[PDB]
Amino acid sequence: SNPKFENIAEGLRALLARSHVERTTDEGTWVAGVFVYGGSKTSLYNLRRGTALAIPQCRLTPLSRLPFGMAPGPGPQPGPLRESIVCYFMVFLQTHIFAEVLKDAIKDLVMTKPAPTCNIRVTVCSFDDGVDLP
Amino acid sequence: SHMGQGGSNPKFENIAEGLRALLARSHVERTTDEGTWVAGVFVYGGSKTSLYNLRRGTALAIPQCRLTPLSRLPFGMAPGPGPQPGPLRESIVCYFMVFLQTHIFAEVLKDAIKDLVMTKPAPTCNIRVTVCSFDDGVDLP
Ligand SMILES: Cc1ccc2oc(=O)cc(O)c2c1
């Protein structure tokens, strides 16, 4: 009933089906993830919905906003709390090996789409002590 | 030290002062020439108000960092009910993330937050924190 989200999920599944790495552990801890940002608010939201369908084993934050980085020139730098218009979401995962596969799959999927979707960025991230999701 | 009207300061200002005191013990690099955002601390739990105060105090204490807004965590094992797929369901537990340019400073800040919140009453003392690492950095705008 949501063909847009399901079609993104299918694109992701086709890429993910080409690898067979473990997505869960007996420990069950949330120790890795992918950090997904840019594009546009709507395109990121749509990707998030498709990720949820394609990967039951993950957990997702809502969209939120990124702060600014460094400003060029002699100043002023932005305050740490200032919010940009660029959005992000986090995917929590139980294995780093699958985080790497998902990062590769997102990169491969979005590059086949027109802007702004192709401007979505992704990096693997790790959590030293895990995140105790409730 | 400075004292506001009536002999008290806001909680976020006292957090800033506490963080400044703890961080002053560690003379580690906070920035790099490359200027890339490769590390962070992920802060969660407590309550929305206690995280709000911690976030505001961290910003006041550390100009070299960048912070996300407060947001909400998904569930772990066995998510709560909802019409949407399990991975998307939101708990009532909140979080924010601090981005940093060095891994050592993320470690120092993680330890400072842990030490500071342990001195505060519940629910602030229930705040949790882990260092995180971004393999390719985050290209903040
Ligand atoms: C793979 C992907 C991700 C997000 C998207 O977001 C959109 O708005 C339209 C899409 O075709 C799309 C595709």
Image: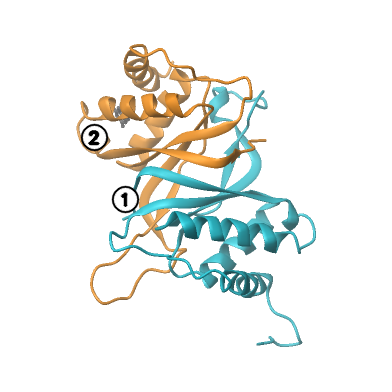
Chain colours: A orange, B cyan
Q: Position of residue B57 (x, y in %)?
A: 59, 68
Q: Which residue corresponds to mark 2?
A: A118
Cβ at disc 2 under 8 Å from ligand 1: no
**Residue B70 drawn above or below residue B32:** above
Q: Position of residue B137 (x, y in %)?
A: 35, 47
Q: Chain of mark 1?
A: B
Give the amino acid type for the residue marked by disc 1 in the picture: Asp
Q: Say whether mark 2 and mark 1 are on the same chain.
A: no
Q: What residue is rendered at 33% in x and 55% in y?
A: B36
Q: Quadrant of ligand 1?
A: top left
Q: Chain of mark 2?
A: A
Q: Position of residue A92 (x, y in %)?
A: 51, 33
Q: Is residue B63 left or right of residue B86?
A: left
Q: What residue is rendered at 65% in x and 25% in y?
A: B77
For the image shown, how many numbered marks are present on the structure? 2
- Mark 1 vs 2: CB contact within 8 A: no
Quadrant the N terminus of chain A occupies:
top left
Along the line of sight, which residue is nearer the eye, A53 or A29?
Answer: A29
Whole-angstrom CA distance, mark 1 to mark 2, is: 15 Å
Q: Which mark is residue B139?
A: 1
**Residue A12 drawn above or below residue A43:** above
Along the line of sight, which residue is nearer the eye, A109 or A127?
Answer: A127
**Residue B41 drawn above or below residue B53:** above
Identify the element where label 2 is drawn.
helix
Q: What residue is rendered at 43% in x and 65% in y?
A: B30
